[PDB]
Structures are given as structure tokens and as C-alpha cells.
Image (tube, rainbow over all chains, first blue to last red; front, side):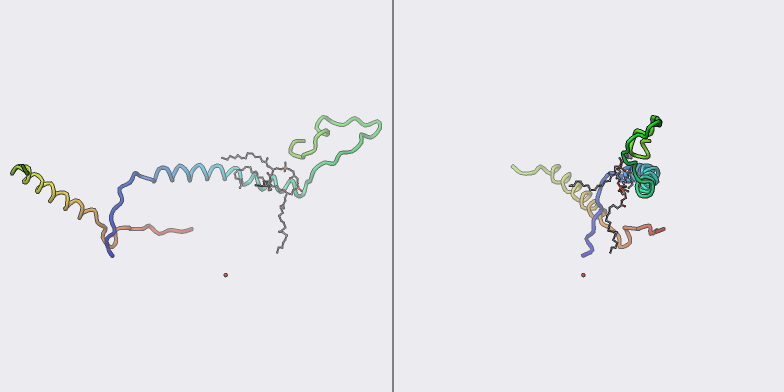
Length: 70
Length: 40
């Protein structure tokens, strides 16, 4: 039945455009961050607690576990 | 009681305008002109 009618509604163009822009920029920075974080965890790994050797004083950044935190 | 002649005439004219508007709200066979584009 060819009774299709026009639906009066406000413009959805600008809302979709804003959502696409925000998604694009957030992803533009977050995708490399997510990939890098995963890569760092997978290959670099995490530091394991160990006793301080005699006569050795560690650096201030050697008291932390995660490589990104270090 | 009942409609006055002016009320009849105004209702009839408004009715014709409203029906023409309602008919004009319909869609042509090509009306949704979609712009096509891609990149068990």
C-alpha cells in the first residue's frame, strides 16, 4: 500500500554530526593509547618485588611496579 | 440551533484546504532519495 506519509520532525543532522565528531576525536587519541597500553603490558611486563642488594641504593622510580608509573 | 451559514462556509473552506494539505503530505515513489556511499 503506497500510503507512505511524510514525518515532520526536527533536524537530526547536527546531533549526529556532533556525536560523530566527538566519537572520532576520542577514538583518535584513545585507540593508540589502548593499543600501546596493551602492548606495554604484554611485552614489557611488570616489575617483580625483590630485596634490595647490599651496598646498592635504588632510584626513586625503582620503588614502583607498573612500567608506565615508573 | 445548528450552524450559521457563515459557519458552514468557513468550515467547508477550511476543510478543503486541510484535505489538500493532507494529500500533499504524501510521498512520491522516489521521495526517500537515499544518497548511497561507502568506503546457523
